[PDB]
Amino acid sequence: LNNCVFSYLPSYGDDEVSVYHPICEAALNQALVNTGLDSTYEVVHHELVGSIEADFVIKNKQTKKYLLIVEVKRTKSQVSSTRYRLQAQSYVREANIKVEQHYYCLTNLEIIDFFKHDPNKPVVSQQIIEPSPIVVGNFSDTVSEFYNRLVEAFQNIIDISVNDAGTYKSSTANLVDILENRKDNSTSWHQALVVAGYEYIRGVLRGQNVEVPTRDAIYFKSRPGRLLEEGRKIDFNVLFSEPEPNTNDNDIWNVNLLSSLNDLGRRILTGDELAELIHDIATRGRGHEGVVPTDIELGKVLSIISQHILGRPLTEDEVISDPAAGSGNLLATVSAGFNNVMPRQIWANDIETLFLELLSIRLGLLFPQLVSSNNAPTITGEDVCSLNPEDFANVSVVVMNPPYVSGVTDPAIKRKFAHKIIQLTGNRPQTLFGQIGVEALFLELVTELVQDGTVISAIMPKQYLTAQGNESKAFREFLVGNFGLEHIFLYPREGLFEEVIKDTVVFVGRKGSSVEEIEVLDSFTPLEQVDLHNLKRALSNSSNEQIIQPMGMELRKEKREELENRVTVGWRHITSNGRVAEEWITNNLESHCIRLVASDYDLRRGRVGNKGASDLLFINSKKKLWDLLDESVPRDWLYPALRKVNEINTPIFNEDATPVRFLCPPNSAYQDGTGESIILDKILDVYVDFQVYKSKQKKFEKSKEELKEILYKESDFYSSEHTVFIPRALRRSARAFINEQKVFCSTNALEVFGGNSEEMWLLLSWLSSVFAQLQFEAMAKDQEGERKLEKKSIQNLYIPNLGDIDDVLKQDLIEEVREIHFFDLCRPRVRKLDLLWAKVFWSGNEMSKTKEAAELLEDLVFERYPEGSQ
Ligand SMILES: Nc1ncnc2c1ncn2[C@@H]1O[C@H](CSCC[C@H](N)C(=O)O)[C@@H](O)[C@H]1O
Ligand SMILES: [Mn+2]
């Protein structure tokens, strides 16, 4: 009977996992029972698929293959969004051979969109399957009717998937086609959007009991000028402008397509569907791109933060602006969070004129009860460098996801922004130093353009927080200057093939202010899990003394003086990433480990080559000397050596690991009469002559007698079998190695010794894991550039209790070392070695705790050394 156990339907602001997921899960299960497919298929919540986690999969019990992937979102605008449709599609691409059928689904429960991934036709809107979009209802509906309809829709979708009976929606496809062919013709592009938009707008508005002109577009086919006038009576001036459609248009006067668009409007009741569809096609000369991909969850949080920095109500004359509006998603989301805004207070601008219509459509239908011929958003298609302070006079809040170009700045773009800033301020840009990015110039230009007190919220690459180039230094100077930084928001973002990523940040300023303490807001939780009601109240209750933390987040305060004085070095000190990692290590690793210093092992800095004559000790390190000497040195006098920690690149430190050699003559080479002493005399002779050759005065004083003694001494600093070596300085590779035979090590590495073969290989296996590396990055929480750790800090590393690993596993752990290289710290990946080690610490859950360490490591490394991720 579909008996519902739920008392309420969600609110858009409810935590997705806590509130939406149980409803969706109960419905999927019921759908399997109703059709009797529960004998064959199971519902799995949070299914790990490669490096990502799916909200729901319908999974075959016997084969473990995927019938259907279901991704849940909170809002209708999210379901319409190409970004989130690509995220859902990604699960099918990541599952590949584990797939039964290529069907996937995106839903906020109110609306279900149903798709079939086809690798030979990857464009999302080409993949919508009939009868999407399925309108289940609205969250203000009676729960039981709504729940029943949810169950029936899932039943339909499951039946179609299991039989591979899906059919691609043709109208969507026909409209995509029409627009793709008009992309390079602004006249016909616009003409198509006039007709299509008229029909879609009328559907959205009629479904919401808003009065619309009663005649359908096709009625005006012979008099299209009338279509323009009929549209203007609703609003959307920039859409309902010239040029008129042509009567002779071979594509747009199609009853089927036009009805379909009107119906689509009736179904969605939002401007989002059509706007996203247009944006996909228009944004094909990409880019067009900005700092982050579409993030509606972020936009919702930004809205709350903006209002809190504003610190007062927005009056009726005050405007909310996005000067590089793009798709309109961010402006639409942020605007919607201001109760009582009028359509006339929203201003969207973008240089790309192909976005004009879609911006009109999205933002005009945003407030469907209010939009009219006298009350509509302003939509402009101007380069920011053409705008003037007067254009921003009424602007009280700016939000932006500024243009970003992942590569090398176009100098003509650079110049165009710089001149405009010079013109406005009389001075060069505060940000234009080093290898400038357009995003910083854009932000600075907008800042100069607005009035004091204007709230400016900008999404920026996180590198700006922590990087040490002159461009990041100048940027932080800008932030605590004119920009009037008040708030820093740190959050995790979602990627196509990566669950969480901390590579972006939000900077919120109030122009011309100089607040004493700057807010730092850190979300430990993905933004979909943030209860928006809790956050609203946490920010506005946080008085002077008592700082109230929102759930899954920490709010802290930093003194401006501290950021001002730490502008060259960076603001890494403000992030919590190092603290949580220290906590994670303590709650998960410490009980089963001991500190290296407590253990039986000895620690010692590499001894070789500390007291000069490096070029002789490492006979083959210098090419010109070696071109001379190579024919003169017996191969068995050469021992594998470490000078620069860089030259090894493998866990096994032997002759095959490195070409670098140390010169160790045998004992008989030092006594007189033998042939060995002869061989050595020859060598030293040629060495002396080359030192002359290199000398400007053709002089070298030091005798063979002395060189003999140095070589004899340094020979005694060899490293015993099964030493494990720790580089003192690393950039990007997780480096640790072991030797099997006698080697020589420079001062550039730390030596660990004392154990036996097995104890030593196990320690190497540990050092090669994400867990040991995590600990290193934690000790280095206050560093930039290379990670430099000496005996002092490494003494304190936690190493696993020897008597805690089972003998089979010990054998698996050592073995695994034999089949790895050095993992990339900027992009760690969970692998057998880590999972193996995970068995020592956890029964629940190996994968998920190993996946956490990996993510924490990645985030810490991104702070210390960004460039490895670009
Ligand atoms: N020089 C310039 N002046 C004004 N706007 C610009 C610009 N260069 C790029 N832009 C715009 O900056 C935008 C990046 S932001 C991407 C917008 C995103 N869809 C959203 O909802 O926020 C692009 O749309 C691009 O057209
Ligand atoms: Mn979800």
Image (tube, grey):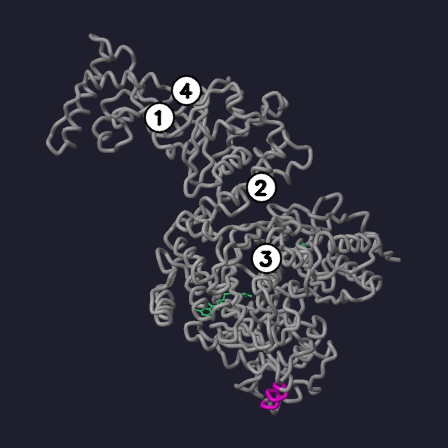
Disc nearest the viewer among 4 and 3: 4
Magenta span: helix, strand or loop, mainly?
Answer: helix
Give how far apart the Cα atoms at labels 2 and 3 are.
40 Å
- The residue indicated by pointer 3 is 119
Query: Is label 4 in contact with label 3 (beta carbons under 8 Å)?
Result: no
Which comes before the other along the chain, label 3 or label 1? 3
Asked whether the viewer can see residue 509, the reply is yes
Mark identifier at residue 741: 4
Q: Which amino acid does label 3 sit on?
A: Pro
Disc 1 secondary structure class: strand
- The residue indicated by pointer 1 is 641
Give how far apart the Cα atoms at labels 1 and 2 are.
39 Å
Disc nearest the viewer among 3 and 1: 1
Query: Is label 2 in contact with label 4 (beta carbons under 8 Å)?
Result: no
Disc 4 secondary structure class: loop
Disc nearest the viewer among 2 and 3: 2
Magenta-span inclusion, residue 227? yes
